[PDB]
Image (tube, coloured by chain):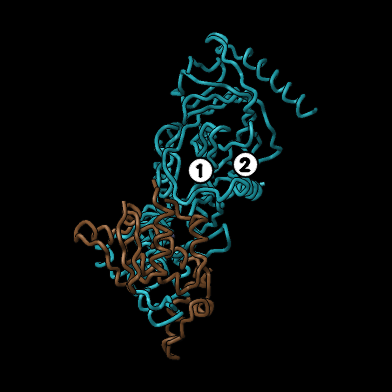
Amino acid sequence: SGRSLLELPPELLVEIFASLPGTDLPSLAQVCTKFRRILHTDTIWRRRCREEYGVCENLRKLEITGVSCRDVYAKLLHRYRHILGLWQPDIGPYGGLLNVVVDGLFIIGWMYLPPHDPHVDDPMRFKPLFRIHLMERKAATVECMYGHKGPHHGHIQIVKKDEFSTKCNQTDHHRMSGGRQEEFRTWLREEWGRTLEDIFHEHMQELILMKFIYTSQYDNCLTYRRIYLPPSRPDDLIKPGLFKGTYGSHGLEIVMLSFHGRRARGTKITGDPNIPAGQQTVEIDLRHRIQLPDLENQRNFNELSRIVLEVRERVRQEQQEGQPFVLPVGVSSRNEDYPRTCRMCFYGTGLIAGHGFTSPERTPGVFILFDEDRFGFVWLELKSFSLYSRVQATFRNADAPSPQAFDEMLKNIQSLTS
Amino acid sequence: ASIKLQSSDGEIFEVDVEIAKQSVTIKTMLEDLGMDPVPLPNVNAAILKKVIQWCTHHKDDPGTDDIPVWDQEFLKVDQGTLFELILAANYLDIKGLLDVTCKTVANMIKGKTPEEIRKTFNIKNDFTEEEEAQVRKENQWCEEK
Ligand SMILES: [Zn+2]
């Protein structure tokens, strides 16, 4: 006989409603009196926050603050769903990394900076740039967390799909009582931990200064473009993600390793004015393994060059139709604490350019795999070594939706810096 | 190997013990209360039948979240029967059947507007003019983008 939905006990109905997407709850709520009333049951929304946005709200916190999960879903989670993820700020050539994330009754824009040069194995430093706070009865507030004088008014604008912007409404807080000299030393201390001096090298001294001045011009009014972590694959792979790498005088840069057939790509997440954020910095030819000779041939620079240009050669013909390691004499390395065993070597090419990314080109070199989360690149024509090491942090909402989508994201961030 | 089940309206069913005990309710009535036959005053005979088919299909069971075909087919019935199954499955405590009958209702709601939901399930709009204005407002946030 002819039962309807409307005759089911409330408890069954809650089961069923608690199982649906949160975005279907608001239609159900407008169907009738009984559904509106039932949909005031927080358990339903507490499940919707957990399963869809990863957040398990505290009940005690909910009681103190007077906020409910219906509120959280509606006014925080869904309202702001599009800025969640992993981002790269648009800051001329320098990039950056923001992971925008849900904690409790907050959404937090976390900036991840590299460790001090040259300590590529030290962990990423991290600080909030902005937060979004839900309180009882109110719309969620937007606040900027830069830089030293506490949280203060901000704005957010979701431009599209894959871009958003922050404004700060009260920059009086970024300032410091000593002035801009002091802003500069604290900044120097956190990014370098070196003395306003120590290095002497006017060149790094100059690069550091200019970067300070260029980025600090974005007070902190920035636009962010979406980026993704690279797809895991079992065979055609030995372990992607983000690494921290030595880039000489520019200091440490963040580089995303990803796999693309029998070829790996090194993509800049942060960069410098020679080769900017968003560009291919490295490419590893994964079918042109190079054999590691004994250790006194390893020491021989020219042996190494002959061998590497001979592979360059054979590569150019086609596109027509652990164990002891040491750098060669003449090859510099900012680190010196690069491992003395390695598994494999492979031919690869780096991207080089003059200042302003002028007249870029691929120079030969050789990629060196040390550990699961440690590798290097010998820059032949610069007689120079780069040591990369895995960024150990973990990132929320950062996965490409699909593989072709990741290869699209690479294409967009490369083009904005073309 | 066999016990007797009694429908709300008198019909008796000889069912295998281990099939019957997928219903935790029955298993309690048989073991703890010693009933044989087990009167099910809330489940009519046509419904009991289907519930015995289901449990029997599912007798061996080591699930996922996506409705197996065999069960989709079992559920190609009319609404009223689908809700009688939900209620029967709630009364008898058969988790698998409850789950699968409820997911099924839920897929019938997935993405519908309030209008389409009322027509699907014949629910009368019982809001007053004010209340309805009020629900609309309370739920604007969903058309945010
Ligand atoms: Zn600010």
- What secondary structure is found at the residue carrying circle 1? helix
Label 2 vs label 1: CA separation?
23 Å
Closer to the camera in the image, B75 or B19: B19
Residue A32 in the image: above or below residue A193: below
- How busy is the neighbourhood of tag 2: few (under 14 within 10 Å), some, or many (20 plus)? many
Residue A35 in the image: above or below residue A338: below
Q: Is mark 1 within 8 Å of ligand 1?
A: no
Q: Earlier in the sequence, mark 2 or mark 1?
A: 1
Is residue A14 left or right of A404 when viewed as pictured? left
On whether disc 2 and disc 1 are found on a single subunit, the reply is yes
Q: Which residue is mark 1?
A: A209
* Three-letter residue code for mark 1: Leu
Residue shown at 54%/21% (left/top)? A344
Is residue A407 left or right of A46 when viewed as pictured? right
Residue B84 pos. (x, y %) = 40, 71
Looking at the colours in the rendered structure, which chain would you say is drawn in cyan? Answer: A
- What secondary structure is found at the residue carrying circle 2? loop
Residue shown at 66%/48% (left/top)? A415
Residue A108 in the image: above or below residue B112: above
* Image quarter (top left, top right, bottom left or bottom right) of the N terminus of chain A: bottom left
Is residue A7 left or right of A383 when viewed as pictured? left
Q: Which residue is mark 2?
A: A279
Which shade is chain B?
Answer: brown
Residue shown at 50%/65% (left/top)? B107
